[PDB]
């Protein structure tokens, strides 16, 4: 019995099926009252919602699904026909995420990609019929934000206006990614100061809009 299994069971027994909002509130209650977990959380989740609403992206790529908290948060705000691709290296987490999406009634909007980002990013065009991405949500290995950003550009997956949104730029922190995007003429950056999920600890999101090469 894992923490992720306990989160999924709590949602199933405390949220309303097909109600994404109740699923998010059930996750946040469980993680505030029982066991901390690396979901983006409500504080940064509110910033994510404001960003999703501004850009109304048609195709979103998420790197790191975990229990599906951020996939539910983003997918519930997507327009009819808009899609989310979420990459998850951990098969146990990928099965929790699918079950979370199923319970929330968002399964038709989200596709889980099983594997490592360095292996899956180059397959996006020919295997997943992707042209360019509207938005990218980075929430995987912190040391991969920079290489994956560079790999997405190499693969021709970024367009003028592609919104990159990165979690945990303060804690655990992504110093090379932050130094790179902020220093690059190919990105327009904005920092959104917030708090680490379920904790009185400063964290933040970085928005980096791709401007072309
Ligand atoms: O580590 C975090 N996330 C990444 C988890 C591993 C993802 C692995 N993975 C998934 C898809 C994928 C594809 N390719 C390659 C690798 C891939 C994380 C950690 C903290 C945290 C922890 C302790 C602490 F004291 C404070 C904060 C908080 C967060 O919000 C986090 O997100
Ligand atoms: K999450
Ligand atoms: Mg995170």
Image (cartoon, rainbow, N blue to C red):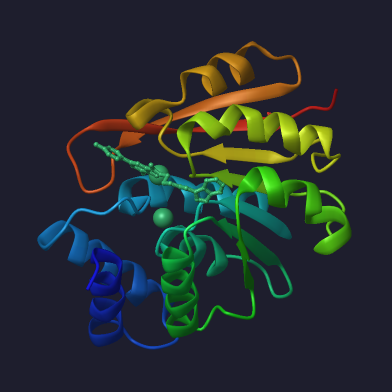
On screen, residue 17 above or below 181: below
Identify which residue is drawn at 21% across, 33% down: 201
Give coordinates of residue 168: x percent, y percent.
40, 35
Residue at the limit of the structure toward the top, as seen here: 183
On screen, residue 77 above or below 136: below
Identify which residue is drawn at 59% across, 60% down: 86
Can residue 15 be seen?
A: yes
Q: Nearer the viewer, residue 170 or 140?
A: 140
Q: Nearer the viewer, residue 102 or 54?
A: 102
75 on left or right of 24: right
Identify which residue is drawn at 29% across, 82% down: 15
On screen, residue 73 above or below 13: above
Give coordinates of residue 22: x percent, y percent.
33, 76
Taking the image as four quarters, which one is ligand 1 found in?
Answer: top left
Quadrant containing the N terminus in the rendered view: bottom left
Picture quadrant where residue 204 is located? top left
């Amino acid at each position: 019995d894992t923490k992720e299994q306990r989160i999924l069971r709590y949602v199933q027994q405390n949220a309303k099926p097909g109600d994404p909002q109740s699923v998010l509130e059930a996750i946040d209650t469980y993680c505030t009252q029982k066991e901390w977990a690396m979901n983006v959380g409500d504080a940064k989740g509110q910033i994510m919602d404001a960003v999703i609403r501004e850009y109304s992206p048609s195709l979103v790529l998420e790197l790191g699904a975990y229990c599906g908290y951020s996939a539910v948060r983003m997918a519930r705000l997507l327009q009819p026909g808009a899609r989310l691709l979420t990459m998850e290296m951990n098969p146990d987490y990928a099965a929790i995420t699918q079950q979370m999406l199923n319970f929330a009634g968002l399964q038709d909007k989200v596709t889980i990609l099983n594997g490592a980002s360095q292996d899956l990013i180059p397959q996006l065009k020919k295997k997943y019929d992707v042209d360019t991405l509207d938005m990218v949500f980075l929430d995987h290995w912190k040391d991969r934000y920079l290489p994956d950003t560079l790999l997405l550009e190499k693969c021709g997956l970024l367009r003028k206006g592609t919104v990159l949104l990165a979690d945990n730029v303060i804690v655990p922190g992504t110093p090379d990614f932050l130094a790179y995007v902020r220093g690059s003429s190919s990105f327009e950056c904005t920092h959104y100061s917030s708090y680490l999920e379920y904790m009185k600890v400063v964290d933040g999101l970085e928005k980096a809009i791709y401007q072309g090469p």
